[PDB]
Image (cartoon, grey):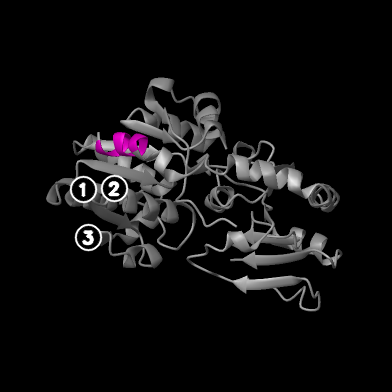
Amino acid sequence: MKNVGFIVTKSEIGGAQTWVNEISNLIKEECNIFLITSEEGWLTHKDVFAGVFVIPGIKKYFDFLTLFKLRKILKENNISTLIASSANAGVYARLVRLLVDFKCIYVSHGWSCLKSIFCIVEKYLSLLTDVIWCVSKNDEKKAIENIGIKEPKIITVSNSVPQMPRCKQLQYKVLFVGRLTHPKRPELLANVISKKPQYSLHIVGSLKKQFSECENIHFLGEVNNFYNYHEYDLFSLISDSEGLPMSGLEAHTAAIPLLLSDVGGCFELIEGNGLLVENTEDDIGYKLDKIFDDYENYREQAIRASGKFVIENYASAYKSIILG
């Protein structure tokens, strides 16, 4: 059986790590999967991995001995495909192509680069990459236009997730799912909803009691396997910076309307099934009332679109990139 490796910087839940976990579950019957990371944490306790390699040197943007340890790992474990996520991981995964033959796949994950300096690096690192995997049309546009990666390098196939449970009378229940630290901005959303007692906010994700006396603001804290989108009426993610957020994809497959910041690839989740916002208290309050005053129309479109980002529709394309 084929040996595939995922290399990441952090092992904490969320973002790329959740993606790695989800993709590993998808291909797990067709290959052996190895994890390479800088630290131990949530991801490294996952049983899907045939083996886990913790190299703390990965936390450094570059380091020769870390590079050589990666080479040793690929060769000794006969790993013929390496899928890299995050900048640091990407640095080692592509430099090590100079030293080892394997299929090197670097995944965009929103190009958190944020500046024309990281852009330069990524452009030249693409020369060492067998596949630049863009997980959103907006990541593809950034790669081609802002970074300078050539299109022959790029395979663009959207992120997607397993279908969340779907549901109910309108209860004006808003749901926020994600880390509470910047660029994420739940404080902005909670503030808006706090002044509207008929609405409510549940936040899933340091931590806050600014709203300790707002009766309609509820912090559930971190919930690792959150799948209860179907209990809520509206998913809202307010943030200064996003790629194509997994939580947004999840809400989408759960057929609930969305209220998202107009950043990164959030617009790719919205057709008639929600609204894009400026991170203004005014703009968020206005578009919130707009959806809730006209709710069944946004709900009908959420329902209509809810098959769009379901991972079964993308599986063969994913498997083709990774196993082909």
317 drawn magenta: yes
Q: Amino acid at mark 3?
A: Gly
Say what amino acid the circle numbered 1 marks.
Answer: Cys
Whole-angstrom CA distance, mark 1 to mark 3, is 13 Å
Callout 1 crowding tier (Cα within 10 Å): few <14, some 14–19, many ≥20:
some
Residue 20, horizontal then vertical, whole percent: 38, 52
Q: Decide: marks 1, 2 in contact (CB < 8 A)?
A: yes
Secondary structure of the residue carrying numbered label 2: helix
User: In this rendering, is residue 35 above or below 131?
Assistant: below
Horizontally, is 99 left or right of 235 in the view?
left
Q: Is residue 138 above or below residue 199?
A: above
**Which numbered dot is residue 31?**
1
Residue 313 lies in magenta, yes or no?
no
Name the amino acid, label 2.
Ile
Residue 63 visible? The answer is no
The image's mark for residue 27 is: 2
Q: Quadrant of the C terminus?
A: top left
Q: Which residue is mark 3?
A: 51
Q: Is any part of residue 322 visible from this angle?
A: yes
Q: Residue at x 68, y 44 (%)?
A: 300
Q: Is residue 214 left or right of residue 173?
A: right
Q: Which residues are magenta?
A: 316-323
Indicate the secondary structure of the residue bearing disc 3: strand
Q: Nearer the viewer, residue 181 or 42?
A: 42
Q: Disc 1 or disc 3, which is closer to the eye?
A: 1
